[PDB]
Image (cartoon, grey):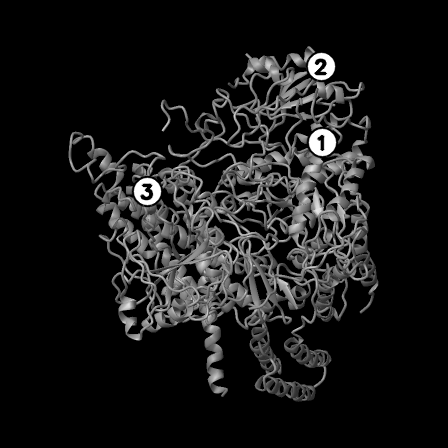
Amino acid sequence: GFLVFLISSLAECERLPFDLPEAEEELVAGYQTEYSGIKYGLFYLVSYLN
Amino acid sequence: TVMNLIEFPLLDQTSSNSVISTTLNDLSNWSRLSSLWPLLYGTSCCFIEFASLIGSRFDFDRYGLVPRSSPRQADLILTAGTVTMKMAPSLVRLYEQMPEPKYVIAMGACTITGGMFSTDSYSTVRGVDKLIPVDVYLPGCPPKPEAVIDALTKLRKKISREIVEDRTLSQNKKRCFTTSHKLYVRRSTHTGTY
Amino acid sequence: YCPTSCLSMTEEYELSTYDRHELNYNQIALSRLPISIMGDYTIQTIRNSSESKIN
Amino acid sequence: KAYLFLFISITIRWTLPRMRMDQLLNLGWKFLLPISLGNLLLTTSFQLV
Amino acid sequence: LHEYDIFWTFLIIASLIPILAFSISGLLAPVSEGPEKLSSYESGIEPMGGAWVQFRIRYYMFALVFVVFDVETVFLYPWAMSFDVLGVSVFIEALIFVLILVVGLVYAWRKGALEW
Amino acid sequence: MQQGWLSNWLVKHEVVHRSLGFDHRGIETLQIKAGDWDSIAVILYVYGYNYLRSQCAYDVAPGGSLASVYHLTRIQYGIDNPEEVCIKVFAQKDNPRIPSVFWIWRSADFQERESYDMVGISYDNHPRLKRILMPESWIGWPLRKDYITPNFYEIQDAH
Amino acid sequence: MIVNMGPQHPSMHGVLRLIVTLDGEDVIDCEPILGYLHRGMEKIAENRTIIQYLPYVTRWDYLATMFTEAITVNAPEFLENIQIPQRASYIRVIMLELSRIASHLLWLGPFMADLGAQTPFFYIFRERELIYDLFEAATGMRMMHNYFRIGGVAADLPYGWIDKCLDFCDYFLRGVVEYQQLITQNPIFLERVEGVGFISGEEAVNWGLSGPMLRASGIQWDLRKVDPYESYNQFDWKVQWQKEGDSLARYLVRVGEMSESIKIIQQAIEKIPGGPYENLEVRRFKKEKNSEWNDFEYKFLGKKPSPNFELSRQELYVRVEAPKGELGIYLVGDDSLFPWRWKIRPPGFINLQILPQLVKKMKLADIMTILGSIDIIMGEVDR
Amino acid sequence: QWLSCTTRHVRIYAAYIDPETNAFDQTQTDKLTLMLDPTEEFVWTDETCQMVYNEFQDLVDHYEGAPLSEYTLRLIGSDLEHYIRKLLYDGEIKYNMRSRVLNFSMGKPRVK
Amino acid sequence: GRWLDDVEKHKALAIYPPHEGGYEGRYLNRLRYQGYYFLDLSARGLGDPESTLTKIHPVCPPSLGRQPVARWYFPPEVDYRLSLLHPDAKGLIVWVYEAKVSRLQVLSKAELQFLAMLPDLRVRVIAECGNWRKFIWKPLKQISG
Amino acid sequence: PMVTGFMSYGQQTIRATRYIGQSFITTLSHTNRLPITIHYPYEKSITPERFRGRI
Amino acid sequence: YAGPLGLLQAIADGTKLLFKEDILPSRGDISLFSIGPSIAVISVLLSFLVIPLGYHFVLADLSIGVFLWIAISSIAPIGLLMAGYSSNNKYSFLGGLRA
């Protein structure tokens, strides 16, 4: 059960949302392109918090 | 008998602010300069060494330079590689579509003048500042991979040279003019089919 | 191809260009006794791969 | 203990090319679901005592 | 199950948090950016126009099978809690329950539903 | 100036090419009829020809007409200096259209496309006959040594 | 229904606008927009001399960084037969077979950063660092600019250069197998790259392709044999190819070729008439008077270099192949010092002709993998 | 669509944008509006820009017979980039004079 | 005003900061509220600095490959900037950024002494040179010679 | 069938693990390696005697 | 360079992101734009309730604790879809739809 939980936890907290330091989050970015200031800050937060 | 004199300073520039209301924006701009992020762009003969700025030869990521591949997010863009007439009408869109604390600079001697593309050719643009207002011009084709970090250190002080009243010089007006046309439309030429 | 060693080389780069039109490099101040990597008191540069010893 | 898993995820970040969403759904559905049901089917009789 | 007053206080506080952050950003912000501001990131000069970009045909099946297979869990939880409390009859009952949906999943697997 | 191996094999079919002489580098040169650029293309591959070369523009003189060039070669496992065949067909500013080999062998999908804007001679047998190098906004045909190079602010003496 | 994949182009090789239809997740038809980086060299190439034109080549050529000067020196020196010694020819062979590496790295590294290999990006740069010191100490600043004059080369490469390959020269040999054991590991590496963008050999030669991307279909059309280029062929080698031609075949053929680079380098350093440069350095002081040294052999320059030289009518072509692809500079043999017309034939312009025909009925991820594996760069394309 | 020559201080917009926001970035592209140097490289008093506004009709009505292509946009921007140069070479207009980088596209002042 | 402790009185000084600049801008911020207004120079490039601070000196523009003699005869930047300055201004705060190491004319220490007189006779100039991690300042005139 | 699946479901996972754990313990010596990359900006690279800077 | 180490770098990036002139693109507005990330942040912030830290340091007994965590973990996708659709163009609509 721990194996399944651990492997699922990756994609559950958006890991990985982009596969490569150069390849984008599958379009240009992960739905946070126009989100510039505190918006992208909150998304960075929520990701780390997940 | 001076030609093209400079306008007069209209304000007397006489004011005094409290430290408890000034050090806030002071440290705010300190963070704004000490947390800058690059914006990815690179085309031609003055770009490739930018990649080496991410490895064990040059590492500008040591200062928190988070390379963002999106206009609306980042604030630092390097016009690396010699720019031509085209790819510019979409380049300036980047500068138009990012938050106001940009403070863009240049990179590549072929982007401040167009050095090795300046005998006769209908493609290259003479410098970049005739397209976008930037702050620092970087020489070299290829640009010296260390001079770019030194110029970043140089620009790192201009932001620290800002005050609380300086956060009003980015507000805009509209010289929007009411003039029409009378001509014939042209259908789209870039038809996307094979 | 210059007659007597006139055109030469150096190596620095602190070009704090705040405007294009400030680049008139005349005779002697071009010398300026430049950075002199070995002549600085905060530098100890170890040779890189192709300049250090083998292994 | 959670720091250990933080570090494990940090390491895994640089060991696998994260799949595309043509394989991710396949893995999440036809791989994890059967075993994540079977472990419960087992632990039922395991906790039967 | 004694005092969720901490829960309510945490709810109101953490719901005030986002609007507080947005308002704090708004107070010390620039009244600027009267530029174009009508187009979004990574776009071909002004690209504009387009619709009917759905591909719902594939992901809709995933959504449906998930919505159906979810109800299993909220029924298992009252059973998963009451195993030792009750006897072993609930064990057989929940086995029949889960096995029904195991058969359902087997069917959804054989006939092509979970695809590319 | 004489015929070639292609003509050596083709004269028996009583349809002869334009028998031109040697090149300058140390090889030979040939020529085909402008309006009959398809017959040569359909016979050469029957002989075994499937690779082009030297897809370039040309001009007759400063203040002259236009032209086009096509060298050709093959690919084989055991090969020893494949035959160097060259064609240089001339054409006038009026009705500047020569057939293309895009529909016989697909090695020139974009090769001729650059000449669709570069010099003032277009070509059929090629869909999407529009500018690529020069911006679509521009209309003129550059690179002619007699063409009026734009005397705008950005070329001539600007002080 | 259709969106552009971005002139910002979140990819390796710069700026590429890809306008493509989108049915939610899968695409139906894509189209490239090129011409945004017009170096216009075809214009200036007439209004210039040779030496003032010499540094111009490694400008639109900074990935290859050396495969532009081969033909750019063939026209001045190899045409009018200003006899290039075989020792300087071997030096140029060292150059060319190191540029093979300069291309292998600057593709595979970014190819690793496109396929899914997230970590080794900085690894290959750390490996490449030594080539920077080499190119710097040889002739030029960083790209070794101006290593080809007309009557030979700029100056014989210094002593701490030739005999001093040994470090990287045996480091990268044991380093290659790292990538070969990593690629077959974690088949998620392999699953996404296998069975995409497959191409056959008959179309590879019918579309005009070249390079290892074509050699990967048993074609073996490797032009490192068909030309007596500077009489290099004294050395031995091993043809690198595959039998599929697809993206995984591209990786195989571009990982199996760099092993021959250091092999040719080892052939040279001990087979060069001068051998190492410190050897020829310590040998030209005991026999300063006369010997095979400084003769038709062992001489960097044959005659005087200068911007003054006339030409006759001689329009010669060379199909000089680079590990990215072929290259050619045809030019109407003109009677004047500078010639009438210039022309270039780059691989990038002869590669994307199949690009819209490659990505057929695929997804955006498939397009990403094919465009990362195809080994394509701008700069060469526009010229 | 909105394919305009958006060069520095020369943005001949091929689409109606003279609100605070065009609400579509084009407003169906039926007016061909223009905004003058948002970076404030030059400070404007109405009278100085009045000659430019008057000659706008000379450039849009007197010498326009070609369809809506950027060819005409360069045909406009060419003389637009030199009307300002003339208006400055006779001292009627001056530079930014603000707290920006204060760049000199035409170089520093002269002594005539 | 810790800078004010060594600018109004001395009118001749050099800034010895750490080689990053991330601690010195706060100092420049305070000196906009007395009558001091910024003039950054990056001294490297000009000839004998006298004719760069007092005289009409022909600054040869970056040439365009052609056009023999063409020099726009540029003006100095002291009296004109005074003319633009209000009559309510204490001093011209100026920064000789390229004063260092650690027909042109080497801007040596004699040239800095001759740029230490315009503060006194007829600009509050401060030389620049990176130094120890602590931001220090020192009268450059005594360092000069 | 399923018996082939009941035999290969462990094989797929064992191949996955034999690759994942192998790469993990191999990159173990990389995450805690003993190389020292480029130092601070006060540690510029060495320059041999053939380059070009300020003429 | 953010002090001795990046111990201040994190909050420095936070403060920098704080101002950054939020843009609020035209198509889609405060009706759903500001509403988007609020659900995202609350879905994970509220989960901190039943998480313990040590011997008698739980914030609430809450016999339905881990159940509440599982329930709150499956509310983020709503906010992600809302945010990704709060704009109009692609690279955010499908970019959020995929996740």
Q: Who's the residue at 28% across and 63% down the image?
A: F3
Residue picked out by circle 3: G311
Between the residue at mark 3 and the residue at mark 2, the CA separation in whole angstroms equals: 74 Å
* Residue neighbourhood size for the residue with mark 2, other residues' Cα within 10 Å, grouped as few (<14), some (14–19), many (≥20): few
Which residue occupies 74% across, 31% down? H94
Q: Is residue C40 left or right of residue D24?
A: left
Q: Is residue K91 above or below residue K67?
A: above
Residue A39 found in image quarter? bottom right
Q: Nearer the viewer, mark 3 or mark 1?
A: 3
Q: Helix, strand, or loop for circle 2?
A: loop
For label 3, the crowd category at 10 Å Cα-Cα, with few meaning under 14, some 14 to 19 and many 20 or more, is some
The type of residue carrying mark 2 is: Lys
Mark 3 to mark 1 CA distance (whole Å): 51 Å
Q: Is residue H5 visible?
A: no
* Residue G236 place in picture, x, y as percent: 24, 56
Find residue E75 and report its horizontal and vertical position in percent: 72, 81
Q: Is residue E56 above or below residue B53?
A: below
> What residue is pinned by disc 1?
H88
Amino acid type, callout 3: Leu
Mark 3 or mark 2: which is in front? Answer: 3
**Distance Cα–Cα, label 1 vs label 2:** 42 Å
Q: Say which residue label 2 marks.
A: I9
Q: Amino acid at mark 1?
A: Leu
Q: Is residue E4 visible?
A: yes
Depth check, front residue: B109 or H95: H95
